[PDB]
Length: 49
Length: 49
Length: 49
Image 1 (tube, chains in turn brown, cyan, purple):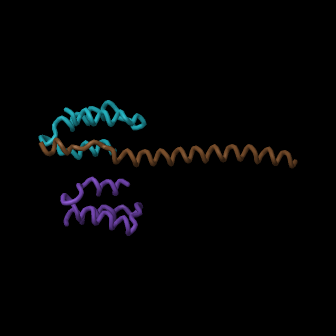
Image 2: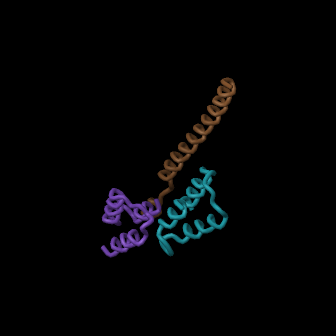
Image 3: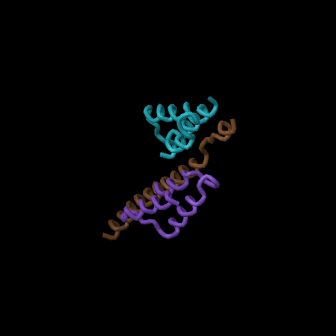
């Protein structure tokens, strides 16, 4: 029974860390999007002309 | 011409973002007639969408 | 002033949207500085947020 508990905890730790990694991926992607918004082209020169 | 080139370059520099051919044509329509039919913001509107 | 009235009449007609006091200040100032500081894009961007 104790070894079964240990195995279950191992598997759950693995899955939990996988989910944490994916959540970090999503946060990184949100930061990427936020960064993209700033890098848009502008019509400064066309406006001046 | 240069600004439209920059706009589409910026679009394709971020493939994660998805622009439909219909959306791309809409951006083309907006960019082509600037200051004769609509202000430049409508381009940024479509990108930020 | 009338546009500010319409914007904040649009918020108060949609009670399901939670505009904190701080965000209301943000929108208020962004409208307050139309065309002297920031185009309309900064207002509707926060509404869309």
